Length: 370
Length: 104
Length: 95
Image (cartoon, rainbow over all chains, first blue to last red; front, side, top):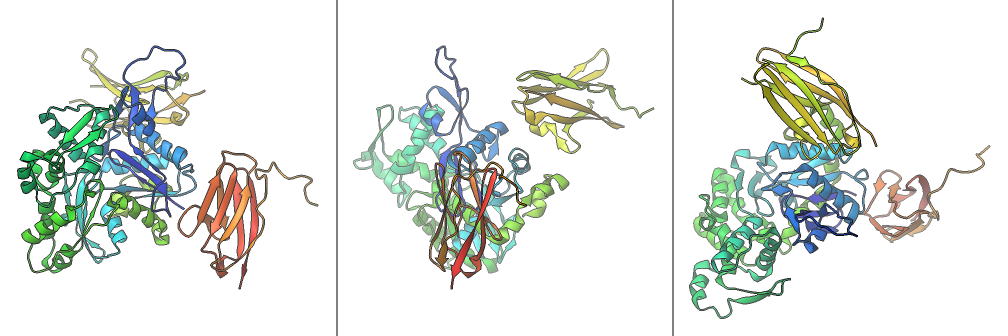
């Protein structure tokens, strides 16, 4: 077998190769006691990791080990990894190779240190760092195309032709589901409800995942939001307090489409996909438009594909028909690509060995893989 | 004898109790010189900075000597080993070897 | 001659040889003498674990190995190691 772990903002996915559903899903958070406690009988427990933190969320000051795909504190990550291998997985790192998934144009230190911790702190014969765009492609079952990867962390585009790569053509987009959550909390304040706490930050995210849906057109529903009958729903908090929202919930997903609300110069996801295609040669452009693949945490809401199809078809040349495939459970699709990738026999030869790391150094990651 | 680097004083071997703190230092004689700390020949301590290991640098004007300190706190078995201190100067390069031991 | 007594064993009950037809499911039941220990499984060529092409079920101090991939090339020897103690069994394949 093999072990596949998804790391990089908000959640940590732990599981076993050979399964299309991981054993352990929990947030990547570490909780410390903000308030000193003067009592007798407590073990004090000055360190909480995982879902336990979620229950004791008010007293604990949550800290995210990973920010923007970059880990601020290395030992917090070690506790998370320890927690995944030993508690939910109930497996030994020694038994199998471990696969980690990483986004394109990510800084060198994250690849070098992450491998370094895996080689030194968790002794394993070999490990490999994979890229989300290539794994999604294998899941798709196509050897040629352009992959749009938007999920936890940073949205990226990576076109490929017959297995040959085009580094110049690869584009990084600063949009993510987590970013939308920050947008959402920011939008709530104007209505008179304010959330400035990490603990309650998740609660708005929970709201966004099921309450929010994608409108056929943003402008027409917002216009019709002046008199909201069915546009407003009541959500129940752990607190027991009641929150009612309207046009506010559908304008959250919109920000990916219209970054101007976020306050950034960079164009939305449909314009960026177009930009990536323009960089590529005209001959290979024709199958790039029909092979667009959507995957990630923020791609969950229905109708995203329908809006993208019309926007891409309108902006793009009419020379070729535009087809976008967005199957359900796309949130865990990246993880799924990793579990299948580890499964292949050929792949096992390709893993970066402990012996190789010590003999040459961290700089060989680029050398071994593109 | 041996060639002269800028370490006026080479780091010394240290002994530390469990959960304690230990300080190692090196002096450089007179822009400011760059100091690197290593675990073994090829492992850099600066990339291992966290709760367990801290780095600090100080300057004394009167002696034109720079004090470089390695701070280790709440020491664990995994940190037992050989550490190498390297100081680079505008015209010369030099290094020293010292060991960190933690028991219990 | 052979030694008088074996080294401390970690298996309470030794997995015993079973026979299965090609494509027929196969289950091997092995029990350890101590709970809290992980038991690795190995085939006459490569290691066996809970992954596609294989299935491992564990509960408490009971380990079950299920192979659905077993066929004519699966004839040989199966080895299972629970901590300090190693024990093996023979899998027979019927044509």
